[PDB]
Image (cartoon, rainbow over all chains, first blue to last red; front, side):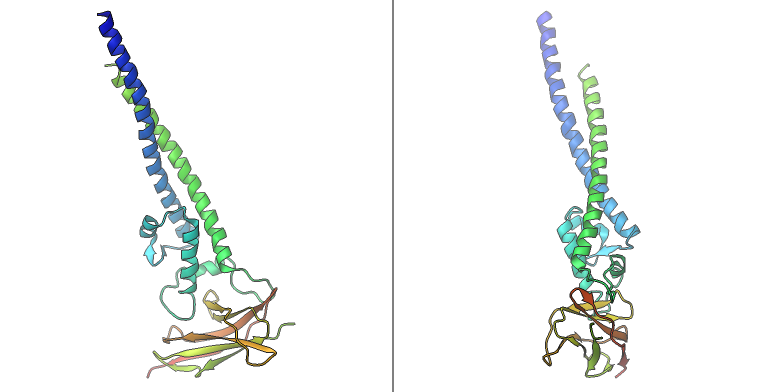
Length: 162
Length: 99
């Protein structure tokens, strides 16, 4: 039945047009997830390896980045700025893990030199760390979104030939 | 060019555990920021809350509300008058009494 065959053949064409759309939305979903988790894992890795930091806001990094996005340069820097001022000061003995940042970032006062403002030093650091993290996250999102789209449009295509 | 700051304590350097102490940094007029440093020089506190005692002087206070033996140790002043940090004060050794 020639017109039967042309009906299925126009059906397979609509399936294939839908499949393409399916395979991109499935790819992007997977890229988003891979991206916003390589970012978290890269920023944590950087704080822990280069800066020996394993907590912020008095939570472990794991929990912290669940509630504030690893790209939120403003609030990351503000968190550090605040934790530095209220845990490396005079008025408590609480948690002095983070205080090393002042040595690292060059804030310790040197008689004979100009003043390095704390918050500007932190936002330079956090901008560098977040840019790094966003770039590796983007590569993860690029790979994973491509790998899923390819597999989906392949799998669906072969399905649309049975 | 910049005179060394001076440091003093109120009520003194030997503090009953749990009670308070205030350090005073004194320096020339026109100071911007007073910094009270501890021996570990990542621990320190800044303040712009400057006052004057005399026309050619300025000063700032640092209160510790509840002293513990981890507060005990050396304390120093240094101040910032643009574009220059001064040199450091003599040390003041804070001690904690049991009772």
